[PDB]
Image (cartoon, rainbow, N blue to C red; front, top):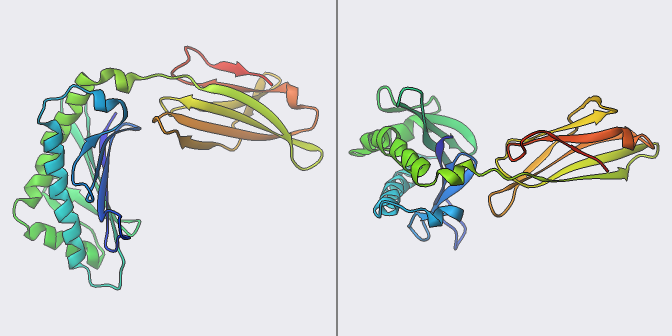
Length: 263
């Protein structure tokens, strides 16, 4: 499970809206929230109850505050009509022999355009705006080193701290509540919806079976709940009156074993 920061900056934020905000993620689970309207990094969900080193959240805040100035600075190096969106995907994951594996990706207006080359401590890209933003970020003192320190030192340190002080939160297994409905689409044909309510982790497989034999996955739909749990539904179209030969099979870590679902 990797720790990731979702960073977003806008050049023309609507009134009462942040110009810059960050969510922090441990796997598929949000632990951090930050925006330029409040200027403070705060815990999310169960992580509010996490016993912490007392200087943790202030250090997350100061780091994100530094990123904030940098992101809003990037816009000044751009000369187009605008508006602009600068997105960043910053983070790390623990590798085999103690070491960690970094992730430094950036997108302009929803299109990937920059990365951070950890080998040489440089921002890289081929678009004129990528070179412009890279140059301005290189010009700022300590900036390249703070990106290095962020990804190689503090990130793996935060990750290890969350795995130790909040192991149970990551290991959370919750089975889905399964349902199977049948509805008539185009006359002579029926549709089956295999639904999965409130599960974690999101890793899940729905498989239809025709009279015990394979029928494959239908057309899947996936989404989150408010508590950080998940929801899915797969759909397969079947001939009328032939519904009761088909059944749904779910595979989930909350279950000890794949479970059949009937109508």
